[PDB]
Image 1: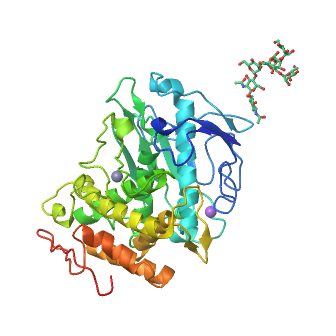
Image 2: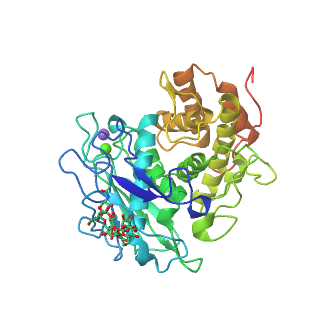
Length: 388
Ligand SMILES: *[C@@H]1O[C@H](CO)[C@@H](O[C@@H]2O[C@H](CO)[C@@H](O[C@@H]3O[C@H](CO)[C@@H](O)[C@H](O[C@H]4O[C@H](CO[C@H]5O[C@H](CO)[C@@H](O)[C@H](O)[C@@H]5O)[C@@H](O)[C@H](O)[C@@H]4O[C@H]4O[C@H](CO)[C@@H](O)[C@H](O)[C@@H]4O[C@H]4O[C@H](CO)[C@@H](O)[C@H](O)[C@@H]4O)[C@@H]3O)[C@H](O)[C@H]2NC(C)=O)[C@H](O)[C@H]1NC(C)=O
Ligand SMILES: [Ca+2]
Ligand code: NA
Ligand SMILES: [Zn+2]
């Protein structure tokens, strides 16, 4: 199979060019490839991890909606961001959406989000959990604009991603080519499944937990787009291309500068917006990630190197600790509990080798030793525990 796409790690069409990629699946994470479910091989954007199509009506049917058919699985369709209208490149759009979602399935699998932990696949090949729950991936979905969304039922019923067209530019911009938005939405599936176990999908339903829900997706999007030349001085926005706005869609850029991004845990007080709260959480995670990269180095290839189940580089280690924390934290967690789950994930993974790097990141932004959740007036702390 060949996919003509912006490769994994390019956040949007401004960061690079499309190329032909052969057989881009991980054979271990996608043992039937992306284009089979173990029963049928599909000459289109359908297989064990997802089914992608256009959805002009914006309704709920998907099985018979349009998707490009190629009997030799050569998915090479035209696209330029200068093209208009979006319907003219729906085939390229569907293929990009399918590619990004399946690449993310494979990375997440490597990080431990597998059939038995509640992932999204049609045929689980007897590896535990409930199947029949690949992701339904709708491109150019007619139910809205200037956004995207993800619906996560309990394990065994499909996730559903709706990608919209953005109308803040002429020509319109198709959100399926902003990998960061795809990754953000898919991460809602990950966090809702892992939190409180795969049978409970209502475990991020409070305002603070819903806030982390938004932040985890912004974080994973930001981690995936990091480039080899980046240092912690790099700032990253969210959705800047699709929204046609250099500030992106959050209040401040993700930055390790407390001037560029002054957010702290106290900024959650009185905040009624999960996207705002999620900006605080993702900013804390950006801090954590760079502490770990500065300590361990960066891997900016599409697969971590794992020694004894531990990523050797800091970027993948950060992603691993964040995903592990999701499975350890209580249902409807607060930031303190989520922090503690990441610390506990590191205890389990490395015997606490990264304790101080984790505490420093969180303490920098008011979630240090002695911080306490309160619905209305949180207790902040910049303190570190003994030894850090
Ligand atoms: C999966 O499936 C899809 C199919 O759905 C595949 O995609 C299709 O890919 C092909 C390319 O292989 C596309 O065809 C190209 O279409 C464009 C227009 O859109 C044409 O310019 C191009 O025309 C050239 O090739 C054809 C066919 O060549 C085959 O058969 C010949 C004998 O019949 C054979 O000799 C040749 O080597 C091929 O096996 C040919 O008939 C044309 O004359 C033309 O070839 C000449 O020109 C090219 C330069 O463009 C030269 O490289 C080539 O050698 C020829 O050169 C001679 O003639 C020149 C004068 O014309 C002269 O200057 C030279 O000196 C020389 O004498 C193709 O028709 C097709 O459109 C794609 N898809 C679609 C939507 O149709 C995909 O590849 C496949 N993938 C996999 C992994 O299997
Ligand atoms: Ca499942
Ligand atoms: Na599987
Ligand atoms: Zn979201």
